[PDB]
Image (cartoon, rainbow, N blue to C red; front, side, top):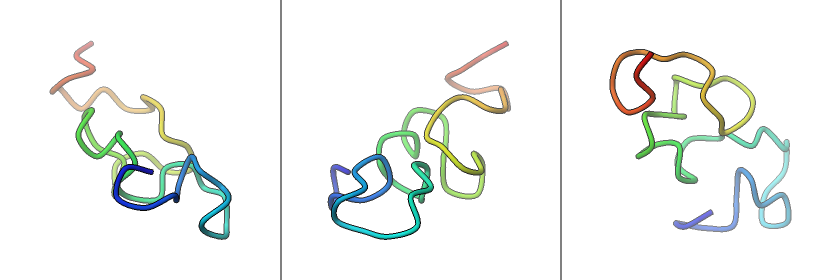
Length: 51
């Protein structure tokens, strides 16, 4: 999204997995190899979205 219109932004990419890598979730915990499909808390991990 922020880097380029991808992930949550469908328009500027293809295969609409809304966690792709960056987006925002990268910083807000992680998306990139952390969340699977969408940019949303899936796993707690420990940091940021603490359980």
